[PDB]
Amino acid sequence: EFISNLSMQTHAARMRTFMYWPSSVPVQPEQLASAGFYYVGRNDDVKCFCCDGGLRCWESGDDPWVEHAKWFPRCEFLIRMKGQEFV
Ligand SMILES: CN[C@@H](C)C(=O)N[C@H](C(=O)N1CCC[C@H]1c1nc(C(=O)c2ccc(F)cc2)cs1)C1CCCCC1
Ligand SMILES: [Zn+2]
C-alpha cells in the first residue's frame, strides 16, 4: 500500500534519473524504470520507488522484473503489474 518514494512514482520521472547511467552496464534504463527502479546516481545502484529495495551489479541478460521478484517478492507494485503468479 505505502509507496517509499512518491517522487519516483511515474516511469517518466524514474527514466529521467538514468541520465548518467553508465553505458557499460549491460541493462537498459528503460527496462529498469519500467520495472519500478530509479538510479541513485552512483555506480549501478538502483532502488524501487515502491518497496525501497536496492539492486546493483547488473549482469548481461538480467531481467529487471525477474530480479525484482527474486529479491523483493512482496513489493506491491511488482505484484500489481506482474501478478502473484509471477512471484
Ligand atoms: C545479478 N543480478 C543483480 C541485479 C543482483 O541480483 N544483485 C544482487 C543485489 O543487488 N542484491 C541482492 C539482494 C539485495 C541487493 C543488494 N543491495 C546492496 C546494496 O547495498 C544497495 C544499496 C543501495 C542501492 F541503491 C542498491 C544496492 C548490495 S546487495 C547481488 C548479487 C551478488 C553480487 C552483489 C549484488
Ligand atoms: Zn519494489
Image (tube, rainbow, N blue to C red):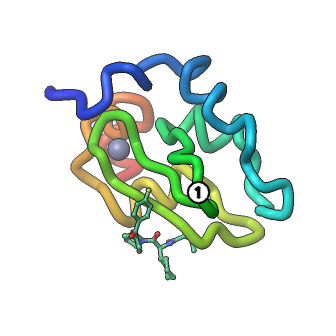
Q: Could you tell me which quadrant the N terminus lies in?
A: top left
Q: Residue furthest left?
A: 1
Residue 64 at x, y = what percent?
Answer: 57, 52
Mark 1 lies on residue: 42
Nearer to us in this view, 22 or 36: 22
Picture quarter with ligand 1:
bottom left
Residue 60 at x, y = what percent?
Answer: 77, 69
In the rendered image of this protein, does residue 39 appear above or below residue 87? above
Q: Residue at x 33, y 29 (%)?
A: 80
In the rendered image of this protein, does residue 75 appear above or below residue 4? below
Q: Helix, strand or loop at disc 1?
A: loop
Q: Residues within 10 Å of mark 1 (few under 14, many from 20)?
A: few
Asked which quadrant contains residue 77, the reply is top left
Residue 67 at x, y = what percent?
Answer: 50, 61
Query: Is 74 on the left-hand or right-hand side of 13?
Result: left
Q: Residue furthest right?
A: 24
Residue 52 at x, y = what percent?
Answer: 30, 46
Query: Is 79 on the left-hand or right-hand side of 55?
Result: left
Q: How many marks?
A: 1
Name the amino acid type tagged 1: Arg
Asked which quadrant contains residue 15, the reply is top right
Q: Residue at x 74, y 35 (%)?
A: 19
Nearer to us in this view, 42 or 54: 42
Query: Is 69 on the left-hand or right-hand side of 73?
Result: right
